[PDB]
Length: 395
Image 1: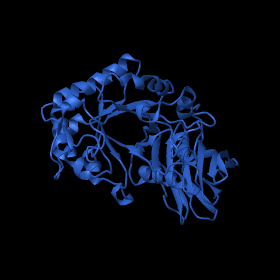
Image 2 (image 1 turned 180 degrees about the vertical axis):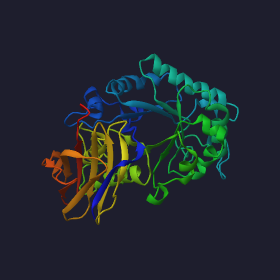
Image 3 (image 1 turned 120 degrees about the vertical axis):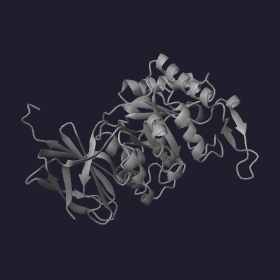
Image 4 (image 1 turned 90 degrees about the horizontal axis):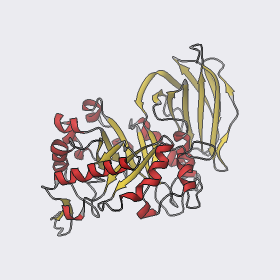
């Protein structure tokens, strides 16, 4: 019942939260949008990770710059994800009685790597140092891009990933299918060439969110959730309540059962995304803000009773002499929840609340009496708490 938050029990170090931009596919973000996405002011998402795509055709690369730049100016990091290598690098092969399936040609592996590097360079030349670049987007769901089998990816990791002058994301499975990435963890050599394990969660059940292999072999390595939308992509859904609570608990789980350090959503602007086509922040977006604006890059998740009451779900982070808590209630019934702070101390507590008729609405300040506080989590809401740790280290 009691949520106890162990300030001492550090888990993963967060890199950020964010969305995808794709100007050719969804139209660029606009100046104003750019900063609804990356500003952290009132009514901005404070996204601190932008994802952009590496376009097979290098004379489109420039499409990416203005928005990257914005992100980079706001202190967000940016990584890039290739869908297809340059068309002349690709052969049609037979995937289960499928005359049509495409793949990188076995002997373009180094050309492909150059192409990646070129992109990383081009961005650099336009004032944008990519944080990371991915080998392939959903290589295991390539019906309409480039297929790569686990062993194909394994070689590129072994023989090519090493070249790329940027951190290397792989292998971006559409659904976190571990067959596509074990080959890498289990190969101390491919493992050397990897910097971030990256996946999507499309249709991945909570039970598949954990990954012992990685926990075993991936020390020094990053875990990112580089793509999902959830719970659906129903055109014009981004304001449904209580539906959008789901986006919230989804991230909850990403963070907690998954130890993902980053959570990247699909299109940022989109009738079904965090920011609606009118420029405006959606309920889904609000569910996203509750993390993205308070759990700043470099914060660290910590142990905290995750599921203290029916439909109540909880996660905690620390940074900046703060502990940020995220408490989600999914009953039609508001609940009094008590919070214990173990191995740390707090002066005071601030909070914001998204419900059916409220987004990121400032709530009532609280003072930490014992080493605990109580707070009511309204029916179908997500509350986020910023606790202020005590000071005498002159800060």
